[PDB]
Amino acid sequence: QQSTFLFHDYETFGTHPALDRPAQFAAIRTDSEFNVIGEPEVFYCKPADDYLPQPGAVLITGITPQEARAKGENEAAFAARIHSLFTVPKTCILGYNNVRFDDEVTRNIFYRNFYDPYAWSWQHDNSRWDLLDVMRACYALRPEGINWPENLPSFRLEHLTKANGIEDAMADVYATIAMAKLVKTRQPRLFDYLFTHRNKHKLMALIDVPQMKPLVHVSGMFGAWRGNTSWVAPLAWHPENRNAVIMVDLAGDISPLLELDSDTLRERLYTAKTDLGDNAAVPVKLVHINKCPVLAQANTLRPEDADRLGINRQHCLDNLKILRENPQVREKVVAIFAEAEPFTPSDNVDAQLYNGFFSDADRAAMKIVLETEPRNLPALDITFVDKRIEKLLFNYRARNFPGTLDYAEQQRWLEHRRQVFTPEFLQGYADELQMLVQQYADDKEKVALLKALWQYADEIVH
DNA sequence: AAAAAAAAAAAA
């Protein structure tokens, strides 16, 4: 057991990790110095017959459902394959924007196919990381030694590689490795600091709530116009999510926090910028310590870089001093999150991963499912406590092993498909394709893609 | 040991 990194990327048929499906997965394993270990893998996932890909996604990836169907395996097999790669001990699974996207795909694919949704990222000394915020952090805090493309800095891999003398899912993986190498070379101490601080316990320690100790925070939510950076201070741990802390963005306008009550603050917080009119935005942001957030002591952002980024230290310090003497603000921000309407998921079991953890007993039961021949599942004498499992099991069987359904199950699946491919859904889908063909009438390649999508839909619904 | 869905923020 030697420590390795497993760089990876998915291409999918849509943006929703629960309701859309993966098309392709690519991975490359390296040692701690980013020398390639073994052989790159890239493989496709065959979409089940109750799904149509989002046209926008296919135009981005160039991957048709026909293509994935032809050279992919079903999702049960696609899941097992990735699961075996991910659960090699002492693996740090990472990518580029994976925490907010690819990792969610992983969790849901495991969930739908009876694998633990999270163990790949913690068990047997595994962990995860994400190079996107590393690049953003390097640009904001220690940009020396690297060339940063702009027009506003860009963090697209293609732009980042071109600007630093460096040469598709597999392509993205190779490029992510190259940026990792670069930053480790030019800013080894920042790199190692970020790597060690992927651990939520090192992060948690930086937060001091009673003191409102200020920190620098680099986040895509701050925006390129300020180099994704600001000084923040913790107001309270989130009342419902123990892995979230409520931060004030010290660079913002704290008026609303002092003036408004929690109900108006909540309303305002979830108001679109373009709907705010006269009113100041609420300068509150959640930091999720289990999501590899970039946090460091306040002085990690040098005055020269605050200046470069257009961030005003005295303004932040001013806000901080005022907040420290207005503790009533803490109560109010917690209320924004504590007194909100609970989130009720839809009755679609695909969307219920976050309803709760499964028990040890259910895990044992799911383990047996995975060890049973599909043809023998119907005869499987077993019982489940979590009410999601029977629903997941029916979907699992119908999507992956349709030959194993009895007549009544066949009829149920037929009704499910009809309830998906309604005349209203099919017409929305037709109108989207027609709109896109118009938008791209001059582009032979995209038009052929849109034609494939129409043909796939026609086939699947007849 | 593991989590939180959407809203909004941002970038794609």
Image (tube, coloured by chain):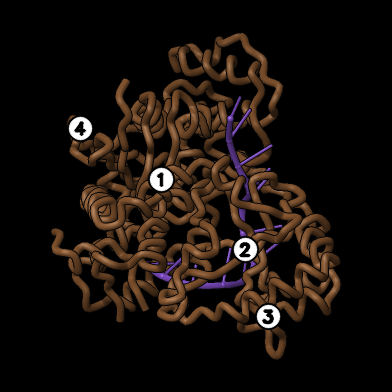
CA gap between label 3 and label 2 equals: 16 Å
Residue where numbered disc 4 is placed: A37
A68, above or below A123, in the image: below
Q: Nearer the viewer, mark 2 or mark 4?
A: 2
Residue where numbered disc 3 is placed: A253
Badge 1 crowding class, 10 Å Cα cut-off, few under 14, some 14 to 19, many 20 or more, is some
CA gap between label 1 and label 2 equals: 21 Å
Q: Are marks 4 and 3 in contact (CB under 8 Å)?
A: no
A160, above or below A405, in the image: below
Q: Chain of mark 3?
A: A
Q: Chain of mark 4?
A: A
Which label was assigned to residue A214?
Answer: 2
- Name chain A's colour: brown
The amino acid pointed to by label 3 is Asp
Residue where numbered disc 1 is placed: A195
CA gap between label 4 and label 3 equals: 50 Å
Dot placed on the residue nearer the N-terminal end, 1 or 3: 1
The amino acid pointed to by label 2 is Pro
Q: Secondary structure at mark 3?
A: loop
Which label was assigned to residue A138?
Answer: none
Q: Chain of mark 2?
A: A
CA gap between label 4 and label 1 equals: 20 Å
A461, above or below A315, in the image: above
Instruction: Indicate the position of residue A58 as horizontal and vertical percent values.
Output: 33, 58
Q: Are marks 2 and 4 in contact (CB under 8 Å)?
A: no
